[PDB]
Image: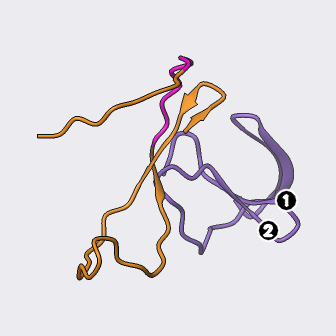
Chain colours: A orange, B purple
Amino acid sequence: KNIDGYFKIYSKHTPINLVRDLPQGFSALEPLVDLPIGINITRFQTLLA
Amino acid sequence: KNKCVNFNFNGLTGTGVLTESNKKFLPFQQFGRDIADTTDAVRDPQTL
């Protein structure tokens, strides 16, 4: 999320027991890092190994 | 601590009695609020 130029990022890592490729329940994502970048973004792409 | 004094915590102004906190705080937390959106606990800008 780009919050007024601050590209704030959230994250969370938990264990699971996969059933249908996306387990359900509830969680809460904590903030990872504040990045006062101030650059406009409109698209993205993943970097797969 | 334990004295009625003013505050300026990197702009977080106020006046009250400073005491030891018994609450937790996230690694990025700056300050906590009460039920009325008023500042209750603050992180020192130089100390953890």
Chain letter of the residue beneath label 2 in the structure image: B
- Residue B34 image label: 2
Badge 1 is on which residue?
B38
Question: Is A17 above or below relative to A49?
Answer: below
Taking depth in this image into account, of B33 and B15 the one nearest to the observer is B33
Please state which amino acid type lies under the numbered disc 1. Answer: Thr
The answer to whether marks 2 and 1 mark residues whose Cβ atoms lie closer than 8 Å is yes
Q: Label 1 lies in what chain?
A: B
Q: Classify the position of the N terminus of chain B by image quarter.
A: bottom right
What residue appears at the point 66 percent right and 54 percent down from the top-left corner? B31
Where residue A29 sits in the image (x, y, percent)? 47, 61
Q: Nearer the viewer, residue A40 or B41?
A: A40
In the image, the segment drawn in magenta is A33-40
Q: Badge 2 local density, few (<14 within 10 Å), some, or many (20+)? A: few
Q: CA distance from mark 2 to mark 1?
A: 5 Å
Q: Residues within 10 Å of mark 1 (few under 14, many from 20)?
A: few
Q: Is residue A35 highlighted in magenta?
A: yes
Q: Residue at x 37, y 61 (%)?
A: A12
Query: What x and y, as percent, mark residue A49?
Result: 11, 40
